Image (tube, coloured by chain):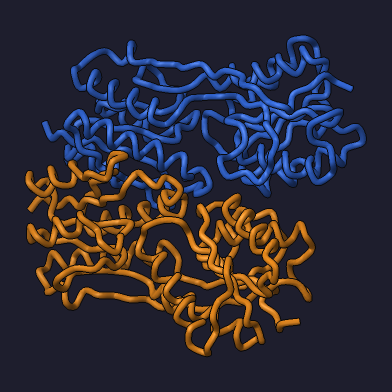
Chain colours: A orange, B blue
Amino acid sequence: RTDAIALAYPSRPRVLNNSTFLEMISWIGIELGKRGLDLLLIPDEPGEKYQSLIHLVETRRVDALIVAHTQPEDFRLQYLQKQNFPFLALGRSHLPKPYAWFDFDNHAGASLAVKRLLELGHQRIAFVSTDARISYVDQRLQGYVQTMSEAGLMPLAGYLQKADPTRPGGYLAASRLLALEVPPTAIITDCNMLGDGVASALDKAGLLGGEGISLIAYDGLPDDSLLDIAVTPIVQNTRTSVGKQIASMICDLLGGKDPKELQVLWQPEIGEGETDGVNR
Amino acid sequence: RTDAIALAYPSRPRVLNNSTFLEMISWIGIELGKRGLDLLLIPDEPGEKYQSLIHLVETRRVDALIVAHTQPEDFRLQYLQKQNFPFLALGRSHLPKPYAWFDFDNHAGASLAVKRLLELGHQRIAFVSTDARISYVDQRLQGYVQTMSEAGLMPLAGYLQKADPTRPGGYLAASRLLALEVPPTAIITDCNMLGDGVASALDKAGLLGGEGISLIAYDGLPDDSLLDIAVTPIVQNTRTSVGKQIASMICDLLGGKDPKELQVLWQPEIGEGETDGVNR
C-alpha cells in the first residue's frame, strides 16, 4: 500500500479546465486527505498520450486512479481496465465490461428542460451544445434530440447549434439562432458559460425575459454574470458534495469491492427562474 | 528521497482559484513530471490551518514544497523556514531571513501603467484593487500610490477603489467612479476580471475608447470577454513559461543550493491597445 491516489485530467481542451473543475479537484484532495490519503495530480501533456499515467500504473506509485473528462471511447480507461488497476471514472465511457463510475444523469437534465418548455407551449426549442468530445456532452445532446423526437417534433435546421463553451460561444450561437428564417421561441444551453452568452445576446436585442425568447441553462448563470436576471437552471450539485462522494467510493474500492456496485448516478433537478415562460 | 513535490494552495478565497491558476498547476505538474518528479496536491481546508502541509512536513512524504498565494505575513512559509524544510514561494512574504521565491514585479507593472497615463496627460487616474490579502495586491497597490506620489499628485477621494476581483466587481467599481463629483479620466485595474467589468460599464455608458475614459488592465481582457475592444494591458507571461521556470528551480533547490540565489523576478511589460489615450 502506497496510500496515494492519482487524479488524471487532460490539459486540452483548456476551456473545460475551469474554476469549477479546480474546485472539484480542491475537494477531491481535502476529502481524501480527511481519510488519510494523498493526492497525486497528473495533468496530461497536450497530446493526450497519458505517459505519466502509464508510468504511475507500471511503477505502482499509487493505489488507485481518478479519471476526469471521460470520453465515449476513452483510451486511458481502456488501458486501466485491461491492466486490472483500480480506477473510478468521473463520467461514463463505453467499455466491454463493468467499471466503477460516478456521473450525473445528463440525458435526464436536458430532457427535463425540454419537457418543461414543451409543457409551457414551445415547439421551436433550439439547443446549444458544447463543441467537445466529452461524454456528458453527447448525453445532454441525446436528451434534447430524443425528447424532441418523442412528442413528434422534427427540430428545424440550425436549432441544434455547436459552440465553443464560452460566453463568446453562446453570444454567437444566439446571434445565429436569431438570424434564421424562423428563429426559436426558446433556447437550452448545455453549460452556464454558454448560458451567459446566449443570455447576453438576447438581452442586447431586448428578447430576454417577458414576452421574449425563453431560456434554460445547465447550472444557471455563472457566479460572475453581469446580468440581473434569474435564468431558469438545470441544477446539478455542489462541488463539496461530490468531492466527498468520490473519496467515499475510493475507500470502498480499495476495500476491494466489485466495480459492478460502485455505480452512483445522481439526478439533476430543474430550478426556478424568471426566464422560462408560456409561448407567445 | 521520495521524489514527490507538494504544492500547497488555500481553498479560500475561492475567486482566486481560477482557470489561469489551474493552468499554472497543470504545467507545474507536467514540467516536474518531465523531470521525473511527482506532484502531490494539497488544497487547504477552508480554515487556512494547513494541517495536511504540516502532516506532510512531519511525515516527510515529500522532498520540497511549492507555496501558492503568498501573503505579506504568511504563517505557513514561517512554519517551513522555521522547520528548515525546502520550499519555493510563488510570491513574496516578509520573512526574518532569505528564502527561495519566484514572483513578477507587480510594483513595476502598476507603475508602468501610471507612467504611461501620466505621459498621455492624465492626472485623475483611478485604481481598482482586488480585495484580497495576497502579496501581489499590496504591491500593485503600492505601485500606483507611490508613482502618483512622485510627480506630486494627491489622488482624489474614491479613486482608489477596492473590489471583489470579478466582472461584477469591476462593473460596480466603475459605477462608483463614474458617480463621483469629479470622475477620473483614466482607470487602472489590477486584474483582467476587474478589467472586463470596468470595461463593460464604460462601454454601456459610451465612455470606452475614443475621447472617453482611458483604461489599462493587468493581463488585458479575459480570453472570454464579450467586448470587441483592445484594452491596453500590463503583460506578465504565459503559464507554460512559468511552470517550466518553477520545475527548473525545484531541481536546483533539491541540488541543495542557497535560497539567497533562487530569487527570480520577471518584469511585466506594457502592451498595445486602443484604450490608452491623450487626456481630453
From this view, report whether residue A33 is shown above or below residue B196.
below
For the residue pair B217 and A183, the one nearer the viewer reads as A183
Left of B86 or right of it: where is B211?
right
From this view, report whether residue A222 is shown above or below residue B22.
below
Which residue does the image show at 30% across and 50% down from the upper left? A9
**Residue B29: in sight, yes or no?**
yes
Which residue does the image show at 66% across and 37% down from the upper left? B195
Q: Quadrant of residue B29?
A: top left
Q: Quadrant of residue B138?
A: top right
From this view, report whether residue A115 is shown above or below residue B69.
below
The percent position of residue B110, horizontal first and vertical second, equals 63, 22
The percent position of residue B143, horizontal first and vertical second, equals 64, 20
Left of B121 or right of it: where is B162?
left
**Residue B126: in sight, yes or no?**
no
From this view, report whether residue A157 is shown above or below residue B257.
below
The percent position of residue A252, horizontal first and vertical second, equals 17, 69
Left of A102 or right of it: where is B59?
left
For the residue pair B76 and B163, the one nearer the viewer reads as B163
Which residue does the image show at 51% across and 46% down from the upper left? B13
Number of dots carrying numbers: 0
The percent position of residue A161, horizontal first and vertical second, equals 54, 63
Residue that extends furthest to the right in the rendered view of this protein: B181
For the residue pair B18 and A275, the one nearer the viewer reads as A275
Check the picture and name the quadrant holding the C terminus of chain A: bottom right
Which residue does the image show at 25% across and 49% down from the upper left? A39
